[PDB]
Amino acid sequence: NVIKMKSSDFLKVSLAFHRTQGLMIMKTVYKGPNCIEHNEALLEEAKMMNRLRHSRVVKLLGVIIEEGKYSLVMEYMEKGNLMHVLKAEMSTPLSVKGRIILEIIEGMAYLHGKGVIHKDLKPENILVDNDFHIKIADLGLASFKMWSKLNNEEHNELTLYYMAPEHLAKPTEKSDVYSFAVVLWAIFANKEPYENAIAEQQLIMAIKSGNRPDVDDITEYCPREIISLMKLCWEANPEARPTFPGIEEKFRPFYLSQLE
Ligand SMILES: C[C@@H]1CCc2n[nH]c(C(=O)N[C@H]3COc4ccccc4N(C)C3=O)c2C1
């Protein structure tokens, strides 16, 4: 269950140290006066997000709901996010990349099975622990309706590359599948796509017209099956994209057979 934490247990987004539980990431969403009577709804949204419990989905450890201060507290993932890892000094072996992909699939299938559409899947929202195991997060608060509203409330002192072309429409599971296709490409390219795009409006129109990440710009070995999977997952028509359970059933035997 979500802990009701107190500031007095701790010494923007910042690393934090709970005086008995240790390292944690804190996002303070609001700091101001008590202009807010969303208290019940803010806490309940936190409880709802905290009920999404899966090994590949981040844990919201606590919430701070105090007089003029509203904070979320999340486990610390010491390797940072997925793009940070892909660009690190030593490369990441193909068997670890394949396991990362499988864990992303499992986490996303869990979320969809609970009726949750992520809407902002991207390497920045894939967090990595020291063992190169991953957790899906929502660091832009696309799923924290109430906390996102509080973040831009009046009395408060405080990405395109992965978006399905229909949204450049009500996000669906298939919107997430498109985002996953581009994450697949980035995992093997070890970088963000579309580096040669000049202008944002150029990129939007190109993607809406059928432009996709440059498969030829992947320099290391990428299995043909993974190339085929990313192309299926970024099909223009969302109804042509598979589901994450359909992806898992194709990818898991391949992972066991050739990547593990
Ligand atoms: C898809 C996942 C479902 C379950 C879940 N539980 N917690 C989060 C989350 O992303 N929590 C961040 C949200 O706000 C932040 C933004 C930036 C940095 C840290 C946080 N913190 C503290 C969180 O708890 C999630 C998403």
Image: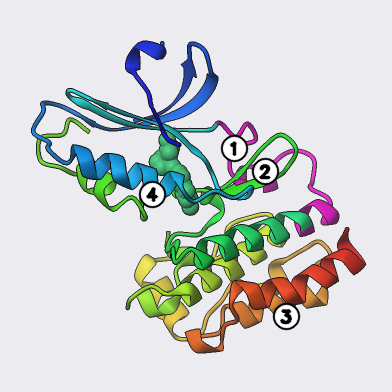
Q: Position of residue 164 (x, y in %)?
A: 45, 74
Residue denoted by label 4: 48
How crowded is the residue under tag 2: few (<14 C-alpha within 10 Å), some, or many (20+)?
A: some
Disc 4 residue type (three-letter) = Met
How crowded is the residue under tag 3: few (<14 C-alpha within 10 Å), some, or many (20+)?
A: few
Residue denoted by label 2: 85
Comparing 165 with 20, the one in front is 20
Residue denoted by label 3: 228
N-terminal of the two: label 1 or label 2?
A: 1
N-terminal of the two: label 4 or label 1?
A: 4
Question: Is the Cβ of the residue at disc 1 closer than 8 Å to that at disc 2?
Answer: yes
Classify mark 4: helix, strand or loop: helix
The residue depicted at 81 percent of the width and 77 percent of the height is 224
Quarter holding the N terminus is top left
Label 4 – label 1 distance at C-alpha? 25 Å
Disc 2 residue type (three-letter) = Val
Quadrant assignment for ligand 1: top left
N-terminal of the two: label 2 or label 4?
A: 4
Disc 3 residue type (three-letter) = Ser
Label 3 – label 4 distance at C-alpha? 36 Å
The disc placed on residue 179 is none
The mark closer to the camera, 2 or 4, is 4
Comparing 217 with 250, the one in front is 250
Q: Which residues are magenta?
A: 76-98
N-terminal of the two: label 1 or label 3?
A: 1
Residue denoted by label 1: 80
Disc 1 residue type (three-letter) = Gly
Task: Classify residue 103 as left or right of residue 19.
Answer: right
Classify mark 3: helix, strand or loop: helix
Label 1 – label 3 distance at C-alpha? 29 Å
116 above or below 33?
below
